[PDB]
Image (spheres, coloured by chain):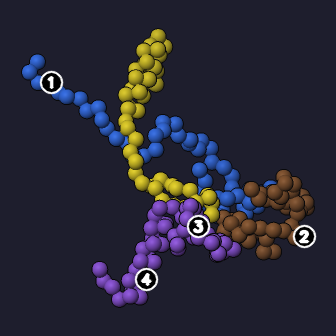
Chain colours: A blue, B purple, C brown, D yellow
Amino acid sequence: LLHADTPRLVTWDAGLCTSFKIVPIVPAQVPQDVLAYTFFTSSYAIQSP
Amino acid sequence: TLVAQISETQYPVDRYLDWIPSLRASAATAATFAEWVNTSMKTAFDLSD
Amino acid sequence: DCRISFGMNGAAPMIRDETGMMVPFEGNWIFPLALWQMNTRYFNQQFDA
Amino acid sequence: SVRGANPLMFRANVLHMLLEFVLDNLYLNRHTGFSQDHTPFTEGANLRS
């Protein structure tokens, strides 16, 4: 009654707001017989979203 | 007169060098450019303040 | 949006013209320099030969 | 069983899950600081950091 724990209601965020993430479930086959590896962009170390 | 050449501004400047490619400089880019101009003029006129 | 697709089974590879058409690797093209700057690695592996 | 759950309580569990979801996503959004794009991938856009 004489003093109650004041809540903390003003807090800040710095990263990007999000709650859903995309995760790989099965690895691809970047070396294969039909299509040469120079086709794919993983062979060039390109960063994809 | 110089900063009006590498950014969008209402100042009438007669706009000579346009065949040379460039990007629309933002505040920070134009600020770095203006700093180089400043230090160059100070060096030329032998100033330190 | 220049995009390459490997021609399979002997067909030549094609590239995505600005008007939507796909064209082989021959003739006379017109690039902006920004394309080659964006894909300096993937382009020369395809074009140098 | 460590791998079993009572089906007659999925609703209560999901209500608690949604409550914790909302309670977790209660933050404000900081303004960090941007940076001009020095490459030709975008039209000189300003990017977060």
Question: Where's the N terminus of chain D, which quadrant?
Answer: top left
Q: CA distance from mark 1 to mark 3?
A: 65 Å
**Nearer-the-camera pick, D3 or D18:** D18
Q: CA distance from mark 1 to mark 4?
A: 63 Å
SS at mark 1? loop
Task: Tell me the amino acid under the disc marked 3.
Answer: Pro
SS at mark 2? loop
User: Is residue D3 depicted above or below B12 in this figure?
Assistant: above
Q: Is residue A44 left or right of residue A36?
A: left
Q: CA distance from mark 2 to mark 3?
A: 44 Å
Tell me whether marks 3 and 4 sit on the same chain: yes
Q: Position of residue D3 (x, y in %)?
A: 46, 25
SS at mark 3? loop
Task: Tell me the amino acid under the disc marked 1.
Answer: Ala
Give me the chain letter of mark 1.
A
**Nearer-the-camera pick, C28 or A36:** C28
The residue carrying pointer 3 sits among few (fewer than 14), some (14 to 19) or many (20 or more) residues within 10 Å by Cα, namely few
Task: Tell me the amino acid under the disc marked 2.
Answer: Gly
Give me the chain letter of mark 2.
C
Q: Which residue is denoted by mark 1 in the rendering?
A: A4
Residue occupying image coordinates x 29% and y 32%: A9
Residue occupying image coordinates x 53% and y 40%: A21
Quarter of image, res B40:
bottom left
Residue occupying image coordinates x 86% and y 67%: C25
Q: Which mark is residue C27?
A: 2
Q: Position of residue C11 (x, y in %)?
A: 91, 60
Q: Which of disc 4 and disc 3 is earlier in sequence?
A: 3
Give me the chain letter of mark 3.
B
User: Is residue D38 depicted above or below B47 in this figure?
Assistant: above
Q: Which residue is denoted by mark 3 in the rendering?
A: B12
- Mark 1, mark 3: which one is toward the viewer? 3
